[PDB]
Amino acid sequence: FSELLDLVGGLGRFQVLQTMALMVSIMWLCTQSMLENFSAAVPSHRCWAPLLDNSTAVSTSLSPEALLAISIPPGPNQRPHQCRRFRQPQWQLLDPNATATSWSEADTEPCVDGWVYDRSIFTSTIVAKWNLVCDSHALKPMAQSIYLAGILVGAAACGPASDRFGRRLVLTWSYLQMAVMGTAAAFAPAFPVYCLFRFLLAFAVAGVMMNTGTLLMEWTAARARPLVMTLNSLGFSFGHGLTAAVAYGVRDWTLLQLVVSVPFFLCFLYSWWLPESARWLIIKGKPDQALQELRKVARINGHKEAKNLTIEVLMSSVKEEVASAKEPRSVLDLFCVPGLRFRTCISTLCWFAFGFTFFGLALDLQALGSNIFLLQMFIGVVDIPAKMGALLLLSHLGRRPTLAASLLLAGLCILANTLVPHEMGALRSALAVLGLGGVGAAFTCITIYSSELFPTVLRMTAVGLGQMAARGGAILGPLVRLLGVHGPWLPLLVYGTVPVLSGLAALLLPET
Ligand SMILES: O=c1[nH]c(=O)c2[nH]c(=O)[nH]c2[nH]1
Image (cartoon, rainbow, N blue to C red; front, side):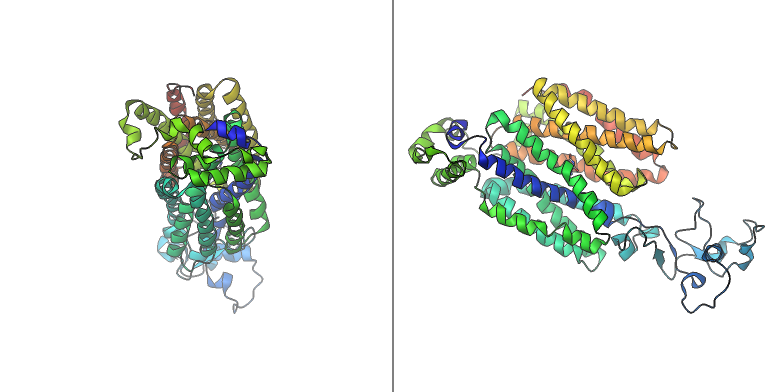
């Protein structure tokens, strides 16, 4: 096919504009995923109580700090209890001499009158709106898990739709669906509907993710394909900083979710403008339109060959592939052929390690550091140079030497969080971010690597399987964090255990 791109211009204006346009959409799409750190942030909270919150209460010289000890028992974390209150005011507890036995456990009651939340950092969050705390606390990681399962099912549905209707035609409606479903999620009346809308949003997120990359590859000459895919990957790195900026600017979740969703109505329009994938139209029985798309791109690049491209030349120049790639085949065919079976096994373990380790740690930054906005931004700041170095190593050594080394180093950095002492907070945050950056370098490496390992028709299906495995690990992520009832030691050890072994296994994969 590349002989035709050589007539159309393999790296001209059109590829520049296409890369820019898709990079922007990928940035906003990344904000859509990372938003959970800010839309669903858990403000500190306590039970409503008369002496603290009754506006009709008789005034006294007692400070709020004293009334709080009079009204809320001490929690096991040595802070005011977040799920209990005193049945009757403990005036006796005002003195410092009071024993722990002064108030009986039977004097405590749950938040009968509801919770009160800290408004200082965020004006509103879903946790504050639907009381996803105490007995309901599990619902937040359930929301994240449902979002990731939505991505998984969307990856399952994208491939067939992409091949049946075209790359750009699926991408366009994925943009529209993201816009509409995010706008609706911003206004959901109750938690079940919010989860429903987030799920239907992730369903389209998956299609955008896959189609943008596939359509970048299918229009770019091979000599610069890795560079373009690296830029498409850096879209997410910049999306991290964009998320930090918007979350700093918009402290209300109902407004933040709307703001990060509206841009996709604009992305819709430019998705309409773009051309459908020429190779797809050529192989899928529509050269008559592939010629029109080709000469559209030629006009944009300014080539004279618009006078040369003709249907007979088009049919002649792709004879080999048109004569052989006539068969659609099921997903399980990736596992039926002996060679593709092993390629898929190793690539799937690599994708699983990426998705597991990254999405386990990237969505709970409130535990990793004292400033969630800055810590969110630092993920992009560290991911940029990691992915550029990944590109350089992938070019000057190869795909195989880069993948294994990146995963091993990221695994080591992840594990180090369990060996540095708890009190050295800054170093722990630094190492966590470094591990995330190494996993990002492995993400870029494998994205390029596994797109080469599979044939023309099934490339999209192979990448979809990669997405599904990575999001299986991602779904296990929040549940691995629900395992945190035994303390943070277990989740971090779990996250660190996988990537090192996945890297050691990666070395068996053939170079491409
Ligand atoms: O390197 C990545 N960083 C991300 O923040 C992100 N988000 C996502 O869905 N895929 C990726 N990949």
